[PDB]
Amino acid sequence: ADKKLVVATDTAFVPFEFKQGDIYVGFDVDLWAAIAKELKLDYELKPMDFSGIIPALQTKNVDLALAGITICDERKKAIDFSDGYYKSGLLVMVKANNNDVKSVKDLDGKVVAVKSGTGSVDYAKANIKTKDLRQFPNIDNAYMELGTNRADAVLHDTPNILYFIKTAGNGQFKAVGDSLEAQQYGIAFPKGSDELRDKVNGALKTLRENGTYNEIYKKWFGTEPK
Image (tube, rainbow, N blue to C red):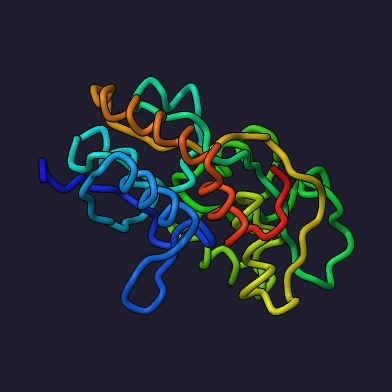
């Protein structure tokens, strides 16, 4: 019973972290619990907005974080990452009856809604000449900026977008283009948590080969490609 690790998590990032009644469920929730079981660790989930997860690690108010955090070189100057646990990317979503946009290129001189503090904003800042880039603390407010056509498209992570269309879009939104900015998701740790980082990486490999990872993956992403 050494102590309870504090695990920072996203308030809403379906299907990796979301609120289901009085508990949190998702891919990251199932994956860490398995990791914490292997390494015999006690922990608590602390959901918060994504823009404060990395600062929470920098200020050492949280012991680690699992929230679709993309492994980035600019972020490694500030925090430590584990080994990738999911290959992801960015994808453009527009309304279902919209046909003038067929890829991210058609989004030049248009209004794009994104989530503040995420990478989708830097990609949009560096590769799209938006007439206006509208940022929202949670991605659900971006969705509405699209549904009511105040914004022309949302650019966010591929699994989040392909799950939102799958579950709560109700055939009102569609995915146009191909996956972009190939990236990998990693468990983030504050600088100086090297012993725990190496242990988590070891438990990661154990679950990748004994099939527990494929068990959790098949649960949320069905017959998703390895």
